[PDB]
Amino acid sequence: VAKDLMEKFNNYVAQVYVLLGQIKGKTMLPLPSHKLTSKDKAHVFEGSIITWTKQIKNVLKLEPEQLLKYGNDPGPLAEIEFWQNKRDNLNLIDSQLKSVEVQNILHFLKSTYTTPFTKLQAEVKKARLEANENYRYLFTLKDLFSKLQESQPSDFPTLYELFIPIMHTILLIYNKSKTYNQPPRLVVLIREICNAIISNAQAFVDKDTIFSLIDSKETTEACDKLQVTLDVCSKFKDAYFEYKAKAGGNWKLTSNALFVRLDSFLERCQDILHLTNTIVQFNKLEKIELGGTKGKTLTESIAQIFKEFEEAVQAFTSVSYDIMNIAEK
Amino acid sequence: LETIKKQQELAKRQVQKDMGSQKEKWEKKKLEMIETAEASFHENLAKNPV
Image (cartoon, rainbow over all chains, first blue to last red):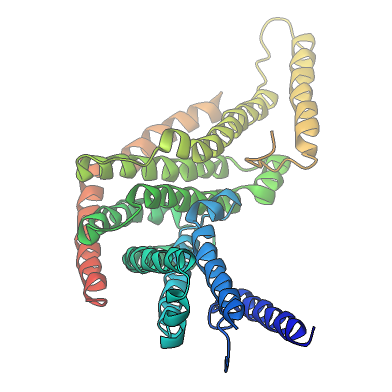
């Protein structure tokens, strides 16, 4: 059991190395490789650890981050940069991983060695594509900063004008790269970044402030401002359409389904605007004093109607939960 | 009714003031200048890795 116990200790050390890579940046294969070897099985154990590292790179994907909310314009660029850095570290790790002794172990029975070596070559390719994606990601990160920096004050009246140039830079980015892998997949990331940025801006405009205004019912210009924020959203879509014409073919995007998230938020906001405008009209009705022909009974009926509207506001006005959440139906 | 009549007079003034001839054209010129500046910046961004 002495040698078996030593092998178990080596496996535990490999697991610790994998844990460091998880908290740390991979490098499981270096930990897997045997140290000061005098057997053949021990070298095979090191090889198995190397296979896990290639699987981890494949497991990470842009789509998985998008599925779990997130998908911010700054975040997508950061994820690409992190993936490129991990691939670069893995490539540097592979050089260290591909030792003279390691090559000899592969020669002494060899299909498993060939599968990891091919996986490493694929990572080197995927890694070059990732580096191009990372340069694109840095450009997107600058775009994200021009949005992340925002203190949620104004911005839409300026951001809408700024949206067209930002869209134009992305159009230029596809042409400059040319060999950029997963170009269609990257588009999905873009639309997700735009919609995610728009949602944060929309929440700041309404949320508690929108509820406080409706309850007071002394603000109208603010209701117009809510429509203006939606316009900014429409301008981004218009700019995106304009970008497609400028792009000339290979439109991709899939906004119809990809833009449904953004479209759903706008539809909910539009319904509030349609109802908010009606509430302003009801306030004017209370002020009206026609005093024509029959009097008082008509006014009492009008007064009840004005009260009726206030009663509806008290139900809607209380707004338990709600707050115009796009997710809440 | 007089207050409502006063609002209508203000309504003509709001449209005449807020809306002006070729308002969109002035906005488009500003957008074109921003696009040209962005294009120059993007070329510089492309240059750093190369």
